[PDB]
Structures are given as structure tokens and as C-alpha cells.
Length: 187
Length: 187
Ligand SMILES: Cc1cc2nc3c(=O)[nH]c(=O)nc-3n(C[C@H](O)[C@H](O)[C@H](O)COP(=O)(O)O)c2cc1C
Ligand SMILES: Cc1cc2nc3c(=O)[nH]c(=O)nc-3n(C[C@H](O)[C@H](O)[C@H](O)COP(=O)(O)O)c2cc1C
Image (cartoon, rainbow over all chains, first blue to last red):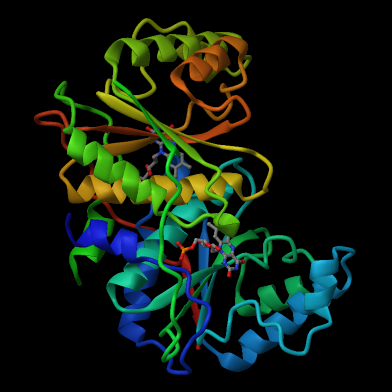
């Protein structure tokens, strides 16, 4: 083992957050870690829009709910008509990770960046979670108008988001185990 | 800074490899790191097929060339008719990372796993590179027959591969810099 290997195993998806905002230096380190992810052809066409403002996060969540309210999926209409659903779990920071959809691997660039950010965050004692609700909603007219106002490029799609914060006091995680049999070694 | 942050910045794509195979314990640590990646809904539907046999790697590369020889893309026909092209750069190990294509985020699961593996490898002094040539070729009949024989599930597509090895003696990398302006912070 080593610190990297242990941080990789220790990374978890956290869905309950303290109100305290993370420090600017930590946010910069986490975003830089995403920036250093591999990208196809070294295109670096991604954008990372770190939203740290509680009012704007709440407004964006309302727009996402509004998009869901338009859906036929029962689970999605239920979110859309909820008075409590918050896709980012009241994390104080959400990083919207977007890319142009030109290359077929566009989302994999983003996932690499996102995984770096999770690991960077874990190494700094900062909880994180993948927030996926902008993938299918980013082209809803009201959601898109909101994203544009935040600085997400209009020609980008949103491939994933990163919630960041401190784990809520007394929030306990399920013990992690992984599926045996995902690995084949051919000698 | 910390070891995780530094390992993240230090990770590079390496395309020249020594002949020495990596140690079994390192390979297991790297694969475990992939296994601990986040996956949508915790489905863990991915498979990791670590191919450590030079003969089989060469045969697989021939099949990939054969698929490319069928293409119209000039760059791909050139690879297909090459006597020297090797998509995995003669790395002693290639990990084929596959998933069922049921969910739209299938490839992002794989990219998360792959990024963990890169970082795990870097932390152990093991060079790595994303090898993308099975994404568009995995359903070619001869390539697919080969993948099946290696143990890649027949219902999976290949979203990315990881070359692993030691960097060739005297192989020098271009200094890494990242694009300024990919980050927007909204306070
Ligand atoms: C592509 C993808 C999308 C995900 N989307 C969400 C999501 O929108 N909301 C959420 O709470 N967790 C999301 N997750 C987190 C997974 O549920 C989590 O990784 C899985 O349950 C394993 O738990 P762990 O991260 O603690 O290892 C997503 C993960 C992946 C990789
Ligand atoms: C989705 C994706 C696909 C890639 N495919 C290949 C490839 O097939 N062959 C290769 O040599 N490098 C591949 N790369 C590596 C990129 O070229 C590399 O990440 C980029 O040039 C930045 O260099 P660095 O990894 O040293 O930071 C791929 C990277 C990404 C994320």
C-alpha cells in the first residue's frame, strides 16, 4: 500500500454535508487535479464551472426539478414535484464538468477529470459525490439558460458534476466492499 | 500539496516501454484500484481483463489492424496495413476495460476505473497509457472472437484499455502544462 492506493479505496460518495464552505486553496487544488486529467488527443476542450453560491445552486436545482416535472418517468416527476429534493445534497460547492460533444469519448474525458477531483478532495478531507442530474436536463431551455448564465459554454453538454463539502457531523457510510469476479488475468 | 495531488500532476501518458513485466502484486493493486472506482447505481457491471501475455497482445493487435484495414479513414487504413503499428506500444500488460452498454454512462464508469488504475500505477513507478483502439473495433467479428477467447464478456463493449509497464530507458516526456481558462469559479 501507499497514500494514493489508500485514498483510492477510501473515496466514497457522500450525500449529507455540513454547511461550511470549503477553503479557496482546497477548491483550487481540486480543480487543478481535474485539469491534469488525461484527455483524448490532449484536446482539453472541457470546462469546469465551480458554483459556490448557495442561492444559485438552489435556483439551478429548481430548474432541474422543472425539467423533471416535464418527464414521464415516475421517479423523475416525483423529484420534479418535490419540495425537498436536492440533487446535490445541499453541498456548499458543485463543480459542473462540461465538454463539447464532438468526440465520442467526450464524457470519458470528463469522468477522468471528475475522478481526479474526487481523489484530490478525499486527500484533503473533503467529501464528494457524482451528481448526474444535468446530463439529461442540460438542454432543457430553462436549465440551459441557467447554465449559460453561470458560464457553462453553450456548445457543451454536461457529462457530470462534483458535489464538494465536509461530511455532515454523524453521517455514517455503509462499509464498502467490491464485487468479486470483475477481474480476469490472462498470464 | 500532498502525495495524491503530486501523483495526479505526475501521471503521464507513456508510449515507450521496457520489456520487463510488472510484478504480480503491483498488477493486483492497480486492478483493485480500478475496482474501487465509483459506478453509476453501484452496478459494478464492468470487467477488467488484464492481458499479460506478449503473444496474445500481438495477436489482438493484428486483429485490430485487420479491422482498421477494412476502414475508409486514411489514417486507419495506414495502421491496418502497417508492419510496425502497435496500438499498445509494446507494453508488457494491457488491461481491457469493458462494460455492458445498457446505461448511457457506461463509458464513464470505465473511465473512472481507468483513471484510478493510472494513478495507482504512477504511485508504484509503473508507466501507463490510455489505449482507445478497441472502442470502434471491438465488434469487428475477428476482434470480437479474440476478445471472447480472452474472457471479455460477449455483451460488453470495450470503453478503454490501460497499457502498463516500465518507461523505456531514456524515453523523455514533453514537459506538461495545462490550458489556462478551463476553470470558472462562481462565488
Ligand atoms: C457515472 C456515475 C453517475 C453517478 N451519479 C450519481 C448521482 O447522480 N447521484 C448520486 O448520489 N450518486 C451518483 N453516483 C455515485 C454512485 O452511486 C457511487 O459511486 C456508488 O454507489 C458506489 O459508492 P462509492 O462511491 O461510495 O464507492 C454516480 C456514479 C457514477 C460513476
Ligand atoms: C478518452 C481518451 C482516449 C485516449 N486514447 C489514446 C490512445 O488511444 N492512444 C494514446 O497513445 N493515448 C491516448 N490517450 C492519452 C492522451 O493522448 C493523453 O492523455 C494526452 O495527450 C495528455 O497527456 P498526458 O496523459 O501525459 O497528460 C487518450 C486519453 C483519453 C482520456
